[PDB]
Image 1 (cartoon, rainbow, N blue to C red):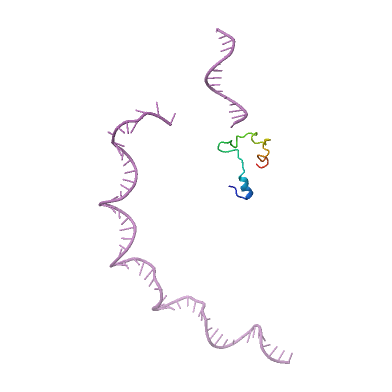
Image 2 (image 1 turned 180 degrees about the vertical axis):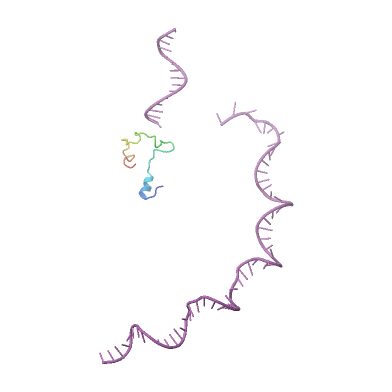
Length: 49
DNA sequence: CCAGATCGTGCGACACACCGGGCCAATTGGCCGATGCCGTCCCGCGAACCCCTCTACCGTGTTGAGCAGCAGCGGCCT
């Protein structure tokens, strides 16, 4: 857990990660899975990454 | 004006300067010689330490991209 301050701890939760066991690895993602789809509106923040 | 500080000079004392004598104190420091406790070693036995061996109802299966070489096949050529 990341405990610099209340905001950092809260933002450690509410995090969606696309890489891990069963996901896609860091070096393999193209440039289409790293884009802001127009369906992100209200489901995933386009600024905070 | 003239009298003590400074110094000259003088007499003595005198603290040693000598360089040579003639004995001594302190203080030895060696181990001398004699006595005694510890290191080393050679067993002595025993606890453990590691290796080898055998047991016979029977039981039968584990991403993308780039570049290059090989196998199968269409189709001439004889």
